[PDB]
């Protein structure tokens, strides 16, 4: 499949891009949604508010965005990168290995949901001098019956 | 590779068994360890206390055991089954889809650790009349900054 970058109605499709030296810019509108799939070594830059964002089946791809009304979902993506300039309510990550997320102050409270994902780090601008601070995302859960009840918990060493 | 069922020193290896109509019985000793790999549609029955148990790369395989000193680990196993007659300290489950665990009263407090696993259920003999009660194992985690701190938690709907 050859490189695809088209707006179909209110849906943008960015697919089949390989080793892109230049940033792939999308001047989007708040009613549009972004779908990025089957891309490798590419940086997608979304300018302007959008309704939703999806990153699917990608390798070493990075996404720079302003804001997303409904959020963003990441599936089967390895070594991905996400940078939010404004904000989004949530980011879902599934079956992905390696990922680095950088949140802006406005987007500090973004919810992150993970499933079968590894090497995921979230960076918050809460260090000294606006500097980022990294938070590695835990991957295991512990489950057992105790104190009369069966409970699940995030495993922490 | 042809069917393998041999004790090498203090290590039992059960591999390459396919559609076994009969239970594969292992009369083991407390100083021995059990490794079950590359098997499909097989029920392994371990009689006697053992040091450890491993179920690796299996499909529709079930394991019946008495007790394990160090526990049991399950990796890349789908539609697996585990039944503990006595007890073990823990069971680790990784990259596995579909699994059903039945714990005895003695083994009621067994710790279960999961990683990239799905459709996992744990049954405790805590219902009425010794009857089992099923506990589906949660698969997602939620992470966010709140109340001055970034925290992770098991997602519950």
Image (tube, coloured by chain):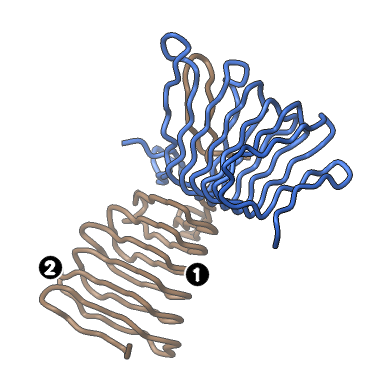
Chain colours: A brown, B blue
Q: Residue at x 42, y 88 (%)?
A: A20
Q: CA distance from mark 2 to mark 1?
A: 29 Å
In the image: residue B42, left or right of residue A29 = right
Judge by depth and name the residue closer to the eye, B14 or A147.
B14
- Location of the N terminus of chain B (image quadrant): bottom right
Tell me if B88 is positioned left or right of A88 in this view: right
User: In terms of image quadrants, where is residue A5?
Assistant: bottom left
Q: Give the residue number, with chain letter if any, for mark 1.
A: A79
Residue drawn 40% across the image and 46% down it: B144
The subunit carrying tag 2 is A
Where's residue B157, x and y in %?
A: 31, 36
Q: Position of residue A24 (x, y in %)?
A: 33, 84
- At x 24% / y 62%, what residue is drawn? A68
Number of numbered markers: 2
Look at mark 2 in the image and give the residue it sits on: A31
Tell which residue pokes out farthest to the top in this image.
Answer: B129
Most extreme residue toward the right is B9
> What secondary structure is marked by label 1?
loop
> Residue A134, which numbered label?
none
Q: Quadrant of residue B114?
A: top right
- Dot 2 falls on a residue whose secondary structure is loop
């Amino acid at each position: 499949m050859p490189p695809r970058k088209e707006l179909v109605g209110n849906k943008w499709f960015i697919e089949n891009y390989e080793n892109e030296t230049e940033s792939l810019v999308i001047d989007a509108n708040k009613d549009e949604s972004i779908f990025i799939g089957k891309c490798s070594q590419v940086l997608v830059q979304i300018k302007g508010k959008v309704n939703a964002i999806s990153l699917s089946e990608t390798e070493s791809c990075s996404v720079v965005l302003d804001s997303s009304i409904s959020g963003m979902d990441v599936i089967k993506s390895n070594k991905f990168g996400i940078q939010v300039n404004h904000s989004l309510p949530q980011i879902s990550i599934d079956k992905s290995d390696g990922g680095n997320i950088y949140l802006s102050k406005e987007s500090l409270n973004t919810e992150i949901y993970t499933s079968c994902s590894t090497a995921i780090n979230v960076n918050l601008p809460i260090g000294e001098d606006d500097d980022y601070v990294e938070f590695p995302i835990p991957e295991q859960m512990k489950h057992s019956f105790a104190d009369g009840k069966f409970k699940s918990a995030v495993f922490e060493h």
